[PDB]
Length: 104
Length: 105
Length: 103
Image (cartoon, rainbow over all chains, first blue to last red; front, side, top):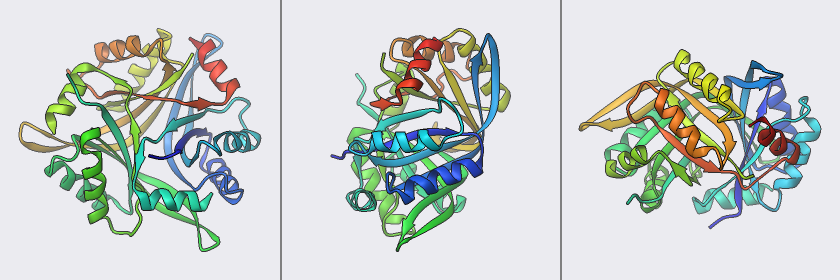
């Protein structure tokens, strides 16, 4: 039904999530971005449980653009190994999908 | 045996509308559950410039057999012309939860 | 190994942090993002309920998914908590590498 995909990326703060989004959108590697602030991320680091504040990003693009988008985000992300995951979209409204493709 | 389940993404302009859209699709049994995350920000280009809106992220859970009708219903009552309507697959899940999800519809 | 994203909700911040802490300590997940301030609407026994919840998003591999859900369900206060798995078709290599290595 669609090659559109959603990319998950974790940002340390709103300002960072903000220009990462602005950046990829300007480059047209993403059609749109949703930012969900107020979260924390837990993970182990050197036998220690780390917790940090984060903003969950949800970007929309396609499989033909996924790699290019990931690299752009990677290059501008302050973290060394930021979370960059691609989730497949099995279906979507036709008008919304057309709008996303047109934006890319 | 359970029918394939999916997660639907949709965004509403405010909490009032989010709860309203959710309550309707749940009443019509087009979705088994809805999670609403307020305070989100939607960024996208429109007419050549970057737009930014405060929105509520909706995460609706239903089955592949209902997705179509769910999307149709959400779009029918949604405040704007072309709302976010994306369907993500659930390749695995707790059997009991998936059963409640299914029986719920 | 293919990785996946797991969605689970907790009735409160403490439960969410405790659930993430133990699955990570058990090395059944690489990381978990906790998002407070959410709401869950659903019908229960013919009634519309709206409960406060913290949205959890956990990252692990397809090899640990079954084990991760069992552990989360085991320690979760609810009898039948939301436990759903979504596939990841692609991802940054270094990140996917770390994710696997963390388990």
